[PDB]
Length: 544
Image (cartoon, rainbow, N blue to C red; front, side, top):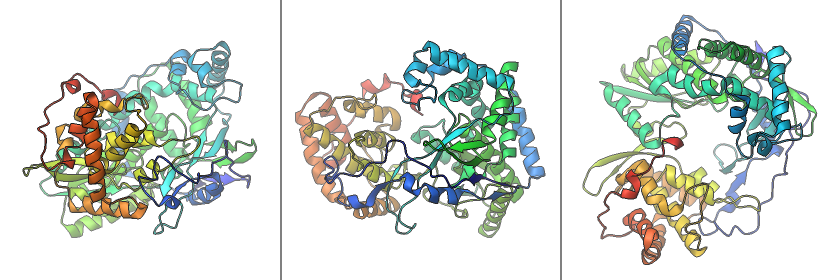
């Protein structure tokens, strides 16, 4: 029926030319040794990407699909959404968002400068007047950092970014922002992935698992989900948006955005030549996350009914998806997943590798991570979110003239605080670097490191500081990842840890608390850690 992309042969071309690595990585050459293995995706590999993502889609919908859609549109109907003022939409632009072809950028937009405002007014008008002319976009290589995978053929090529001009982006929000805030929750309820913190994601999966008499779970991904989205899928999204109570202006606005932007349109490289034409999901438009999540949800829910998945509970993180249901016997279970996959494929949403039924929660991966179990010092099982540390570690080792990894360290420490690799490797390194630099309280991305104990307590609870015995899977993976990157093994970290712990303790104050709480696993004679008052008086609902 249609190709995801047509190309012209023009090259997809960098902005600020990707930078060579330096002969010394002073912040991380004591973290690991195999620096030769950490690499960053460049536009040089962008053709290789484009090939992987360009293919023919044909889609066959059915009664299950129709039925699911009817249900969702009824759900959407209960939502009412407002317009955002041009000004409000401007204020939601991020500080460093890509400046505009019309001599102004984010600072102007956020400060409501007259010409920025003015231009957007015209952009919005043209949207109201013209429902047809496709709106042009730029395509860029994403630069991300990985550890080399010999298994999966060396170096992943870059991801492709496709976005309209800043003027349009502001406009998108006037039209759709409020819907992005309300629609997903209303169509999917608890299935919606982005609402939860790690601990809550854990809890939900556990609850889901627990309520099946005889549970079975699987995850489904596709690497290339955007490519598989059809013009029709996109129009179906609009129709879903339209089932809401909107003002009329917004309805027009949305239709135009669908017809002129979302459904597809032409692509230019930064050099400014025509590069190709897109007939699938745009990587950088407002609706990308909402849209993928909803469309994925519709397709998956239909496919469950097609396959006879019994009593399914879903978690949806975009392209990424977990289903936990009632097992029907493993032989039936294997059959129903083949059927699910076949149905998904008819819907134009094939998988990466085919899914597989599992009967143990540790073996189920999604939003790139998994639930694991650790034993408190007296037997109690605690469950918590974790993942393969390889990428976190490669990212932790990426240092250039224009990039520092300390941020990346702290992000991981927070999200994965209960993990053995965070607690033994990253925590130990982070604190040691900051102490030597004497910047133990400079603020990184809005968080002060000396507040980790309370933040971690607030987020993960006091168990985060007493996970005593980790699982075989987890021990195996971590050890293995460390050997892979040439990082010291856990035993060496434990040493480093003891000395970090001491320095933090002698430093007194909040440092001493970091010492006591974060590094209690490092000493055989444990301090009794009690709740931090600093922590109850603290709200991070904002973050997850």
